Image: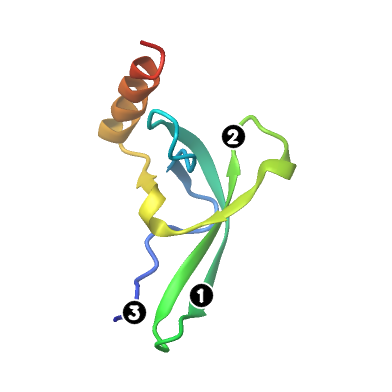
């Protein structure tokens, strides 16, 4: 395997996928609290993104991988709205 690149920064607003795989997919508006560089068993770098879920108390804060995060673009905001509606269908 091979080094990740850090893709998000402290203070950034990002959209985070629901981790529960039993649930219809939805995105949560989140804030990056910390970006921590680690190396895996192969000696390659990966990043742990500690995030806060906007509108929730800090006890809900979690560290996640880049794969579950999206940039806060208009297109991803629309995706979030689409998914939220579908979850309610």
Of residues 63 and 10, the one drawn nearer to the viewer in this rendering = 63
Residue on which the image places disc 1: 37
Residue on which the image places disc 2: 54
Q: Are marks 3 and 2 in contact (CB under 8 Å)?
A: no
Residue on which the image places disc 3: 3
- What is the spatial separation of the Cα atoms under label 3 and label 2, in whole angstroms? 30 Å
Which residue corresponds to the image point at 39% horizontal and 67% vertical from the top-left?
Answer: 6
Determine whether 39 is above or below 71 in the image. below
State the image coordinates of residue 13 (x, y, percent, origin top left).
48, 43
**Element class at badge 3:** loop
Q: Quadrant of the N terminus?
A: bottom left
**Element class at badge 2:** loop
- Mark nearer the N terminus (3 vs 2): 3
Which-is-in-front pick, marks 3 and 2?
3
* Mark 1 Cα-neighbour bin, 10 Å: few <14, some 14–19, many ≥20: few
Q: Quadrant of residue 78?
A: top left
Image check: 16 left or right of 11?
A: left
- Mark nearer the N terminus (1 vs 3): 3
How did the renderer colour the structure?
A: rainbow
* Mark 2 Cα-neighbour bin, 10 Å: few <14, some 14–19, many ≥20: some
């Amino acid at each position: 395997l091979r080094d990740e690149t850090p893709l998000f920064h402290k203070g950034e607003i990002v959209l985070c996928y629901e981790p529960d795989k039993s649930k219809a997919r939805v995105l949560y508006t989140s804030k990056v609290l910390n970006v921590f560089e680690r190396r895996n068993e192969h000696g390659l770098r990966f990043y742990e993104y500690k995030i806060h879920f906007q509108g929730w108390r800090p006890s809900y804060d979690r560290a996640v991988r880049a794969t579950v995060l999206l940039k806060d673009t208009e297109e991803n905001r629309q995706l979030q709205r689409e998914l939220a509606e579908a979850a309610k269908l």
